[PDB]
Image (cartoon, rainbow, N blue to C red):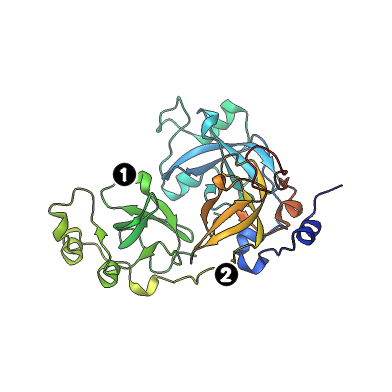
Amino acid sequence: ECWSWESYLEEQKAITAPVSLFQDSQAVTHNKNGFKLGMKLEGIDPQHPSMYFILTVAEVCGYRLRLHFDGYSECHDFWVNANSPDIHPAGWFEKTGHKLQPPKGYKEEEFSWSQYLRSTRAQAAPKHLFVSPPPLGFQVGMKLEAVDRMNPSLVCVASVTDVVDSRFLVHFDNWDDTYDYWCDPSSPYIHPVGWCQKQGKPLTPPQDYPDPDNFCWEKYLEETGASAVPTWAFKVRPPHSFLVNMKLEAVDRRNPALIRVASVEDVEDHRIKIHFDGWSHGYDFWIDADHPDIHPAGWCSKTGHPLQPPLGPREPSSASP
């Protein structure tokens, strides 16, 4: 007897997070996933977002796919939705002037898609599969203040270092490019030059900036000849309207192949804390409300992905009865 949301909600006297609370891209279930095992493509390294690698479709599940970094260990495999903006068709880097980190074994200048496909007897994922208007007012080289996602109490001197379709790459000046992240104008993690000063919050200057206590934006902009992103470009998104106890579906962070029945455990203006029904609180996690790996109830069913029901009552890792 199939698990259903309808039955569960009745048993629990619970409600779902309405579809209207989600971004269209989190909610859309009627798109076909045309990706197939073995198809090759290009994509950002999710753990080093300024970098591009050749990827192979290693698995397809509903509207999701597992991607493998050609030549490298399976330990780096990762899952995306078929509407991910972080993947691109073969030829994208050459067409757009980006650099490729070639497959393990390969030198960069010797990489050719035509030869690679020959050598691997593989096909490139067709272009029509890929979702990826400019972000108005955001251009490469402009400066801003941004939250370091790896150190979230810090608001920092940052630069736009790339623009791809509707998004841009946020870079922390003179810091490791592994702190980079992709963004759009509505991000709550970014602010105009001078925001910290106006808020009475400390600003983290560029790494090793001489006399960092006397860092001054006007001098720094003069030094670099860079412009600030204009204030008009920043488009404040409203706080989300998820409420505690609302039910939804979320990818498991420990085993990202899995999606589970989930509840809103806590809320901030722009983030929700997920609890997996039936589980210990040890696994609860905070996630951005626009994160691609949360979805409304029914998403798995409608897209053909399995949904893990709540953990049974006296199981290891289970919550109190």
116 above or below 10?
Answer: above
User: Which residue is depicted at the point 61% across and 60% down?
Assistant: 25
Q: Which residue is mark 1?
A: 176
Where residue 203 sits in the image (x, y, percent)?
26, 60
Where residue 127 sits in the image (x, y, percent)?
61, 48
Q: Residue furthest right?
A: 1
User: Which residue is depicted at the point 55% across and 49% down?
Assistant: 284
Left or right of 8: which side holds 147? left
- Disc 1, SS: loop
Q: Give the amino acid type for the residue marked by disc 1 in the picture.
A: Asp
- Disc 2, SS: loop
Left or right of 95: which side holds 303? right
CB under 8 Å between callouts 1 and 2? no
CA separation in Å, label 1 and label 2: 35 Å
37 above or below 153?
Answer: above
Left or right of 51: which side holds 203? left
User: Which residue is depicted at the point 52% across and 55% down?
Assistant: 287
The answer to which of 279 and 175 lies nearer the viewer is 279
Q: Which residue is mark 2?
A: 241
Where residue 235 sits in the image (x, y, percent)?
44, 71
